[PDB]
Length: 231
Ligand SMILES: CCCCCCCc1sc(N)nc1C(=O)O
Ligand SMILES: [Zn+2]
Ligand SMILES: [Zn+2]
Image (cartoon, rainbow, N blue to C red):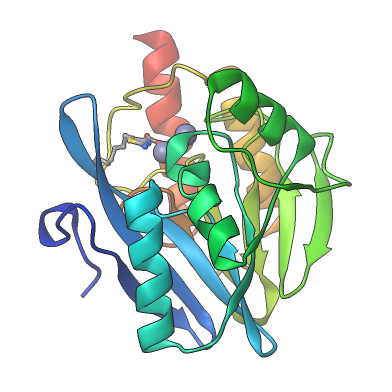
């Protein structure tokens, strides 16, 4: 029932219910000659919705907001981007134009700027160092250290024990690290552990690409990362 890359034409967005008031959103996009799926999160925030991450581009992010409105019907009032790449900030200008207040860490916005990506409007304070946590309406943002990228956040929904790993967490189906350009493979295993350490109660674990899972996804990524520093 979880939608796969071949079932989502580029430009469409699926929503998938994970728990009460917690959905993921799944889109698809070309990168370097192939199309990949991508997840973010939607969390009910009282009478509003918090968005974790764009749907990877302006057209995708538009289709995201239209599906949200058709299937859920509450306004998206804020969004957080969890690192600076395009599958996370690409679409922030569409969100801004729709009326969404967009947020990321100061590191993330700096790095988006340097890279030429869309820049979320508002800075998130309190996340500067490996281990920091802040409350953000119905979720907790947490900086576990460098992994996929030096800025990558993860997100936890306490009410529903959902842990969103962003691109720092892989799906079991996946066995090569693939593009790790902006990564830090020395710190990545240690950063995955700070998560295991802070969220041992996590029932649902969502990587940035592919199928949801449980905490086993943590260890699975560590291994797939180590496999690439050895060779
Ligand atoms: C089983 C194949 C699973 C998909 C590989 C993803 C490769 C891409 S594309 C993009 N925008 N981000 C990534 C990433 O690794 O974070
Ligand atoms: Zn990335
Ligand atoms: Zn990614």
